[PDB]
Length: 358
Ligand SMILES: *[B]([O])([O])[C]([C]C1=[C]C(C([O])=O)=[C][C]=[C]1)[N]S(=O)(=O)[C]C1=[C][C]=[C][C]=[C]1
Image 1 (tube, rainbow, N blue to C red):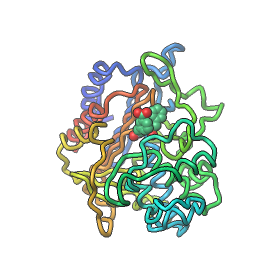
Image 2: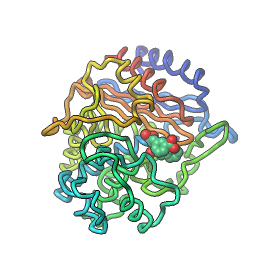
Image 3: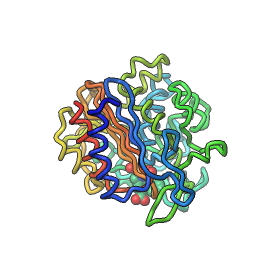
Image 4: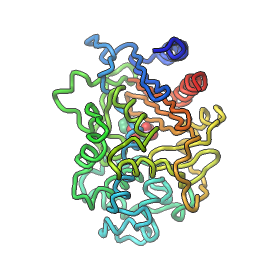
C-alpha cells in the first residue's frame, strides 16, 4: 500500500487492538477504488492460526446489508413491493395488528416495536407464526424506529417468497455469485472450516448459535477480500452488470426515514457527508443505536446520495465488525475482529482512517 495508507491504518489499529484486547483483526481500505489489506493476530488462539486475507469472520448484523440488497434486488425484479402489506406474503398472519404493516416497515424497523431478538424458544415455521401473531405493537406503523432482528429478519424471509428459492439459495445466486463473493457463506462448508476464525467472549472460543431468522438478520460469514469487494460493489453499483442487482444496491441506500442526523436504508444506515464524527461515533453506541426513536418519513425516499457516510456495525457474541464508505470519494473501510468490542471504538477508528485519506 501507499505509505500514507499504511501509516494511518497502522497508527490507528495497533492501539485499538491493544486497548480492546482483540485477538485477531483484518482491515481493508478501499482508496480510489482499489483495496488494501491488513491483518493482525490470531484466528484461533489455541491452534496458533494467524488471521489471513482468507480468514472467515462472523459479520453479525453487517449481514443485514446483504439482506437489504437482496430485498432491493427482489423489488427491482418486480417480485415484491415495499408498499405491499406483510399479509400479501404471509396470509396466515391474520391478527389485526398487522393491518397497515408493510414490507417497508419490516425492512426499516418501523413496524411499531417488533423486538430486538426473536425469542430462543421460537424455531419452527409454526413457532414463528405464533410469535408474530401474538406480538402487540407499542406504536402505530411508521412512527418509531426500534432496531430489531425480528423486523428485518422477517423482511428477508418474506422478500424471497415469490422467487421460490430458499433465503440462502436466493442470496447465493442473486448476490454472492454475481459479485464474485466466493468465500462468503451463510453456512460455512466443511471445506472452508480451516479458515473459520473462532470468536472470543470472556476468553472462550465461540461460534454463533443457530436461531430463527439467523440467516436473514445475522447469518453471514466472510473474508476481508470478499468484504472489500462488497464495499466496492456498494460504492459503484453502476459497474455491476446484473441489472436488478445494480438497482437493488441503489434501493438499499435510499433514505426512507430520518432520526436525528441518521437516515435508514435497507440494512445500510446513512448520514450526510461531511459527517460530524461525534454524531456517528456517539451515534454508533448501542445507547442510541438500539433505542426507541420517533422517525420522520422521507416522502418519497431520497435516492442514494453520493455525499454520504454509509455504514453498518455488526456483532455476534464472539465477533465485532464495521463497514463504512463514502461514495463521492470512492473511499471505504472494513474492520473485522474476533471479539465483540464497543461500537464507538470501531467508528472512531474508521473515521480517523477515512478522514485522513479523504
Ligand atoms: B447486530 O450486530 O446489530 C445485532 C444486535 C443484537 C444483539 C443481541 C444481544 O445483545 O444478544 C441480540 C440481537 C441482536 N447482532 S446479531 O443480529 O448478529 C444477533 C446475535 C447477537 C449476539 C450473539 C449471536 C447473535
